[PDB]
Image (tube, rainbow, N blue to C red):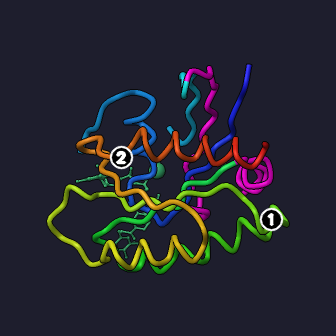
Amino acid sequence: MTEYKLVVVGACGVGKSALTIQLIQNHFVDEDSYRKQVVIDGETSLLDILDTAGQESAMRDQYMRTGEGFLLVFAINNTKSFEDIHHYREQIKRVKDSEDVPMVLVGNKSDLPSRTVDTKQAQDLARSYGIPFIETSAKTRQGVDDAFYTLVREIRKHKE
Ligand SMILES: Nc1nc2c(ncn2[C@@H]2O[C@H](COP(=O)(O)OP(=O)(O)O)[C@@H](O)[C@H]2O)c(=O)[nH]1
Ligand SMILES: *CCS(=O)(=O)NC1CCN(C(=O)CNc2cc(Cl)c(Cl)cc2CC)CC1
Ligand SMILES: [Mg+2]
């Protein structure tokens, strides 16, 4: 059976755990690792997921090396978390020693009325990186399946 090792990275508090809990366990209430079989485009896929901010080492650096795809998560009401994205992407590229690593940019907390990061800013950044941008809410489930499944599709594209 096909397995995908996914890593969800981003500043603390952006909702990495909340997004992964919503995907895997289907709930939100206002575990660092998760493992579940799902079906994506008719392919049975075992998802092995790690949520990490990088400040919590061994399992982490290992996780970055084996990770096949990465969600780069910021929150739309956290400018610093958006500013941090470049650091996370550069870190992954260095560890993977590759310019072609499957990634998706995720702007979480889209349900909130407080916004300090413009959708255009995020779209522009993702365009520069050549990766998808998806607006999500772990609370309402907006974009959650789309974010993770898009990443799995990026991994497939890489492997093809
Ligand atoms: N309103 C809202 N709150 C969220 C969302 N995602 C996460 N949260 C809340 O933001 C806080 C931090 O979320 P958490 O999953 O622990 O962030 P992490 O440090 O990135 O894993 C918690 O109080 C969550 O309930 C979201 O999409 N919308
Ligand atoms: C994901 C974050 S964590 O698990 O690594 N823990 C963080 C929680 C948020 N935080 C804080 O500093 C918030 N609090 C405070 C801590 C301290 Cl030491 C002081 Cl002096 C004051 C506050 C409140 C402002 C970072 C770690
Ligand atoms: Mg967490």
- Residue 106, image x and y in percent? 44, 59
Residues drawn in magenta: 42-68
Q: Which residue is mark 2?
A: 143
Which of the two discs, 2 and 1, labels the residue nearer the N terminus?
1
Q: Residue at x 43, y 43 (%)?
A: 146
Which residue lies most toward the left here? 113
Q: Is residue 41 above or below residue 134?
A: above
Q: Position of residue 39 (x, y in %)?
A: 54, 22
**To which quarter of the image does residue 53 belong?**
bottom right
Quarter of the image with the N terminus is top right
Image side of residue 121 versus residue 70, left or right: left
Q: Nearer the viewer, residue 56 or 19?
A: 19
Quadrant where the C terminus is found in the figure? top right
Q: Is mark 2 within 8 Å of ligand 1?
A: no
**Residue 6 highlighted magenta (yes or no):** no
Q: Which mark is residue 28?
A: none
When asked about the image quadrant of residue 140, the answer is top left
Q: Amino acid at mark 1?
A: Val
Between circles 2 and 1, the one closer to the viewer is: 2
User: Which element is circle 2 on?
Assistant: loop
Label 1 near label 2: C-beta < 8 Å? no
- At which x and y percent is residue 145? 42, 38
Mark sitting on residue 95: 1
| Mark 1 Cα-neighbour bin, 10 Å: few <14, some 14–19, many ≥20 | few
Residue in view at x 78 percent, y 43 percent: 159
**Residue 36: x and y, percent?**
56, 24
> Does residue 37 sit above or below 130 in this rendering?
above
* Left or right: 114, with 25 as reference point: left
Q: CA distance from mark 2 to mark 1?
A: 28 Å
